[PDB]
Amino acid sequence: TDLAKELVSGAPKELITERVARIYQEAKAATQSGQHNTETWKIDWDILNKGNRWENDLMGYQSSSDYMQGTILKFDTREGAIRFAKGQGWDYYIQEPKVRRFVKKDYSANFY
Amino acid sequence: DSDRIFQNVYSKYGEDLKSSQQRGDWYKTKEIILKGHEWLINELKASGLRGRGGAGFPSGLKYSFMPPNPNREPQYLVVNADEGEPGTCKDREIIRKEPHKLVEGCLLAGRAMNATAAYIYIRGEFYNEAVALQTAINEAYKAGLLGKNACGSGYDFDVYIHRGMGAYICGEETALIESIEGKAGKPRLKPPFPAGVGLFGRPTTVTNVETVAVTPTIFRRSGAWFASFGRDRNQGTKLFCISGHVNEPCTVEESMSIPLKELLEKHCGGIKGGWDNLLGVVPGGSSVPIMPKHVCEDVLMDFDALKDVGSGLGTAAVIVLNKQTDIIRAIQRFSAFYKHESCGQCTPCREGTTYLQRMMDRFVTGQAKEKEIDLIYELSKEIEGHTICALGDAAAWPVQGLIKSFRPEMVERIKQYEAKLGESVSYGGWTSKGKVLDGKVVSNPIPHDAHHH
Amino acid sequence: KEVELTVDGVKVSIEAGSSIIQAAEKAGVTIPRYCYHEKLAVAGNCRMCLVEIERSPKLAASCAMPVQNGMSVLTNTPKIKKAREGVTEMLLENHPLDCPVCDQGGECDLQEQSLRYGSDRGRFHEIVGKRAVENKAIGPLIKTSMNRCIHCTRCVRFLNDVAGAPEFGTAGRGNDMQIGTYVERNVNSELSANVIDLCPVGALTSKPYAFRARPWEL
Amino acid sequence: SHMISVHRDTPKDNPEIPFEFTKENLERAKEIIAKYPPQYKKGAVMPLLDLGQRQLGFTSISVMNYVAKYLDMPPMRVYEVATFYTMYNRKPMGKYNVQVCTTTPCQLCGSDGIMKAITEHLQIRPGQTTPDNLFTLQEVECLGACVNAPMIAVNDDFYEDLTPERTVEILKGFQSGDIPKPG
Amino acid sequence: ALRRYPSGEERCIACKLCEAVCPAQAITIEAEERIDGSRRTYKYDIDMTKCIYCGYCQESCPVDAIVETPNVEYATETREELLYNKEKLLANGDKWEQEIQYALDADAPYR
Amino acid sequence: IEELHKFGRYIMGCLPKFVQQFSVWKDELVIYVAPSALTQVATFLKDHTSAQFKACMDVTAADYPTRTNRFD
Ligand SMILES: Cc1cc2nc3c(=O)[nH]c(=O)nc-3n(C[C@H](O)[C@H](O)[C@H](O)COP(=O)(O)O)c2cc1C
Ligand code: SF4
Ligand code: SF4
Ligand code: SF4
Ligand code: SF4
Ligand code: SF4
Ligand code: FES
Ligand code: FES
Ligand SMILES: [K+]
């Protein structure tokens, strides 16, 4: 836990001093009634304020310089995500998932 | 067997109030009302009366579910006075020929159910019956038989007439309430039940005309006499609407458990063309499946004897089919009926009835394959038991009845149809040359049977 | 007021009067649904949520059947698997083959639930064809392709109860029943566009967003 | 029947055409409402629509809006009721609505012949209207008069136990101006 | 190549199936409502230096809009010429339509 | 499946000190051991007459960042 495992991972120093990762649980999509994607905790990185995306003039391609733009880690528990982020010495913040309040729902309430 | 419940079934005694009293309709009305619902419920239970609307449910048992009404809260009673079902001609005659008999039954039944009002739901096609029934109701109001003082008794009771505008689905009890409340008239899901939450959010009971009209006699001639007719637990008399391939169709008031063969031969002449010319019989109504000739030879009119043979005694609507008839087209007509009469809220019957109608159209001409007989049978299974109301079940039995006992006759059409076309037909009615060009399917016989229009 | 019921051998406890589909979610059991939404009134017009009550000869719709104490609910028996395939086949009987040109493609509940619970093959070869429904015009925000509707009444329930706009309803009877406003008019509501999210199929879609993207790209 | 769930504005049927119950129907409508509890007055839509239909001739869009305003209800709620029931004619229709039952009990006793004879006499296919706006042929489901299976309906009147030669006489009576004996 | 209907209308409805299947992610598609309201693409790029010539886009196409011609003799002096846009792919479809019809008439039954 | 269950149980019985658990999937048997037990279990599975696994066909790893020990 306290071990600074980033000294041996080989990742560049910019992951620690310049990038911010978000630990979050995916919110339920408003267009679908499934909840499978909300059962896992994920880690992604905030975009670079400049150079995240720019248009290549030759073909209109989406050019980028962020090498972490397409990396999304998967975790089964919130504690596991925190332990891994702490182990790598990342600057992170946790977005607590919104919980749906339970309200009783019955067919009789359509008239009463 | 004379001295039945109904005596004016032939329009020979008048449709007035006085003749009804001379017929015994309004007799001892004060005493019966003051006997309390405890005795009325027990008599109905002890008379073995069962629901005449099609379900066949104990009338006495379904009246006790109504909660007591000590504070005179507005409970309701609804009379299912619309027919809807093809081949049924019972409710029309009771409303027309004996309008005052039903009105007397509503008050006596209402007293048992603790009902403060009665709503009669009659078809829009029965305008003459509704006008005649309204005339009887208004006379009973002036005579004091209806209102806040029912023949001196303190039981206040009102009667109203609500007219539908044409819907077979409105015959169902929950859909009937929706029509009265001013909605489309789609059946409700069973919980909460109409006994607890019904018309206007009040306790309610929905009963057939043939069930309410028998109540006055049961309260007078005792439940023992009514229970004497029929076999065990099928106790009572029944009005039978007989029509089709018969000599002289009519409506008779025989008793339960009477053999089908004797009933069609004792009166109504006989089968048109003799007994050897009988192809099939559809009792109860269009909902129940058909029965073949040999089965009908020993069929007793009961909610159980007809249940055993694979059929149902819904409304005693007996439809006779001689051998010189199109049996598949007759069943196809039933499928087209339920497609048009489907209210269309649940997925199964909104789609299944259309699915059955499309497949039955190719069967009547033979533009299908023999394996598709099992396909349409499977599609009917996907409808039963997956619907809010029973119209989905009622739309699958006629097709299954055709398959069960008349499958070889359906195969004959397919074999005959291939002779004319030469090459065999593929699934769905497609040939080896049929293709779509410029907005239409060409080079293929299309079954144009969707009522054209 | 809690009642201890059973869903596929799992103990559940919820408030009295809760629907079975609510107790199943609390127990971790997933039941397919089209017409049920946890913010709208209870409807039972889609029949996709059918479950088998332990001691009862009838299949109950879990979104409308109230919970009882001691009730044992089975949701994965072969009888229910038959019901899910049968209801799926009815839904896709008249549905147009529009997935490539339909904006709900990658986020369609009809696609995913037909894949998960329906059969892999269809049996509709009828030469008469499917039902065809004209497209209603209800303004510049909501794009209508009414061939794709499965008659689930999510839009009707939302616009009448939540949004408070009673100009949207169901007109017709049977297979000819059509969702819309009957007359030629628009939907006047500041929350009308939420009908696009609630519509599980491509019948109601965003008009500005039409054709411009697929959900897996975003 | 002819089931259309969409209204299209026409000079004959459009919301601009004013409609209002006559002073005779204004009073009779009030009795209808009195047959329902005051807090459930919305249950009187069905009788009010038929009251307007008989007065005007058919269930126009002006009648549906008039009933909606009369009962303090959204117009769409009245639209749902009018389009769900087949006896609400959402088109001008003729003087006499010819309703021929084609169900199995009526089909056995030769209801097909009844339809054939009428089609070649009035020269209008089912669902059409005679040029003089006098007749209207309509295919209808069971009407309950199945014991007398060869049965037809004209407006509000039934006609049972018919033959192809008898149906022409009934049409001839209405064409001439004489009411045939119903039975 | 991008193919047309016999009336000249483009077959592709910008359904973006080929872009999703493409193992090398060699296809870039941008789409919107056409001027007349049709669902059409206005940008269809294929990186021939990135494609692995695997046929997944042809298999996934619901309208047979994107196909692979039997052509192989199109080596180019510069790598820029191997960046096909919609104009290049549509021109290829017009140029090679007859040869594509040969292959389709013999291979479609096996698909 | 049944034969591998019996053989997998025989290894745990022979090495209760090292074999944490075993699993069987169709025709594949997996033995789960601690890092301090790898040498002993591999030596047993190589030299025992009933289990002569002389060939080590593959050595690989998989990353599971969720767990305290990332790699299997
Ligand atoms: C689709 C459908 C149509 C029905 N039509 C009628 C009808 O026309 N007359 C009737 O008495 N019951 C009809 N029923 C049955 C009623 O729902 C109910 O069983 C009956 O009205 C109760 O009255 P009872 O106690 O006399 O049986 C119908 C049921 C269904 C599903
Ligand atoms: S089964 Fe058919 S008729 Fe009955 S409620 Fe459902 S959709 Fe309506
Ligand atoms: S709504 Fe779903 S199933 Fe229907 S066409 Fe669109 S993506 Fe396909
Ligand atoms: S349009 Fe969409 S939301 Fe409305 S009933 Fe149809 S499927 Fe449901
Ligand atoms: S053939 Fe080329 S462009 Fe097509 S899917 Fe395969 S790699 Fe992508
Ligand atoms: S798969 Fe075919 S139709 Fe779909 S986007 Fe690609 S080329 Fe267009
Ligand atoms: S989700 Fe329960 S019937 Fe639709
Ligand atoms: S079947 Fe024609 S009136 Fe009943
Ligand atoms: K949608």
Image: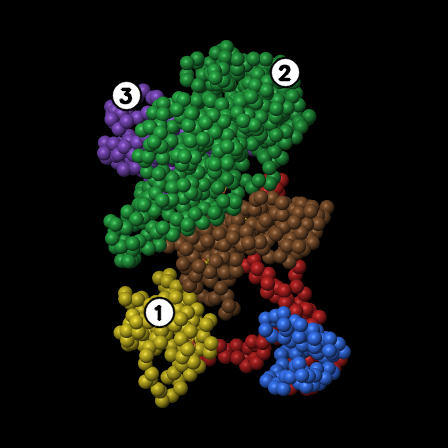
Q: Which residue is mark 1?
A: E110
Residue C135 coordinates in the image, percent (x, y):
40, 52
Quadrant in the rendering for residue C66:
top right
Q: Which residue is mark 2?
A: B153
Asked whether mark 3 lies closer than 8 Å to ligand 8, one says no
Q: Which residue is mark 3?
A: D178
In the image, which lettered chain appears green?
Answer: B
In the image, which lettered chain appears red?
Answer: A
User: Is B215 on the left-hand or right-hand side of C70?
Assistant: left
Chain F rendered in what hue? Answer: blue
The amino acid type of the residue labelled 2 equals Ser
Measured Cα–Cα span from mark 3 to mark 2: 51 Å
Asked whether mark 2 lies closer than 8 Å to ligand 1, one says no
Please tell me whether mark 2 or mark 1 is closer to you in this view: 1
Above or below: residue B425 compared with residue B267:
below
Q: Are marks 3 and 1 on the same chain?
A: no
Residue drawn at (61%, 85%) of the image: F56
Q: Is residue B315 visible?
A: no
Asked whether mark 1 lies closer than 8 Å to ligand 5, one says no
Callout 1: helix, strand or loop?
helix
Chain D rendered in what hue? Answer: purple
In the image, which lettered chain appears brown?
Answer: C
Residue drawn at (72%, 46%) of the image: C1
